[PDB]
Image (cartoon, rainbow over all chains, first blue to last red; front, side):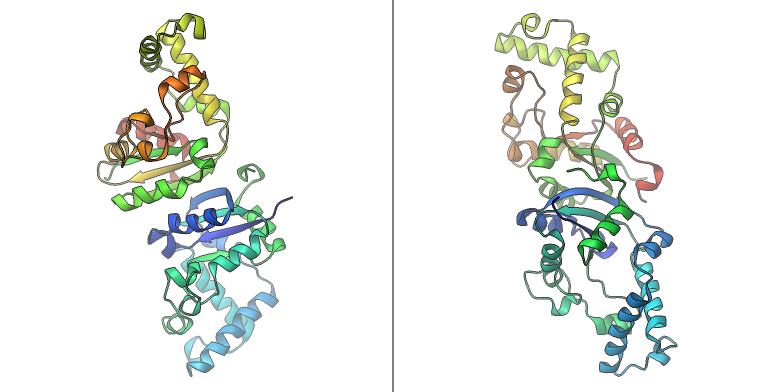
Length: 182
Length: 182
């Protein structure tokens, strides 16, 4: 039962005309788009889309605490807390603004090892350090320090399901059974 | 208040991987995509999307009849009737079968004089005489003789609204207010 993954083009990405450039890369690799739609998500939808586990909030929190040390930013002065879970809730809230600020395009990609292949093509979380050839490296120059100073998340173009399991959940979230056509 | 039009990539064109190539031509011209979805359409849906006016059936019918005549096909031996409206109903059934044969991708394109622009970019009905530069001349080599010989419609990649009037209708038909995003 061939593997599927969910990909979202975030609002900067759509507004900049990158839909077709990004679709072209998956196509050329041999992935089929088996669902596709442009949507305005409400904050509610984005809130339930992203996890709410403590583990996730916590692990997103440390990434940014680690960041704040390197730039010498006191997180207490910057966002009012140094608590990892609380900082996670602030990141999630930032995520919600950004994914809510314009239309998204959501697609399901299907092919041998879709989930890992899409992560590989998309590239790492920071575009400034994503290698050339990757979607994030070829189409963005944003960086986690700029994001930290401007009080936002990184504008890294897309979200890709980080696992088979997470993929089945995020797919079901966006698409009813008969919108996914194989 | 700026003009919009409805474009459908038909199953052949979705299957051949032309979604991104086609989206690229519109983005380059300055049109914005304001609605986009991949859909598996039912027979009844396509039945209702295409007109059922005698006027429309009649004219669809004459074009095929002219086609048969230049080919020296007897429409009575070929399809059982030579009545323009009855022929239009046969074409409509063939239209339905083809648009129903796999996923379509429906989009709404907004920009100055969108309907003509998109009609201009797409090219005339037969890809075989569509000039190079147009969507139908660059991506298809189909022709009405072959289609006739083979008891089917022309595989001409797309459907474009043929007037603003018809566009406001084809737009409502496929999208709720909330999906056509302003």
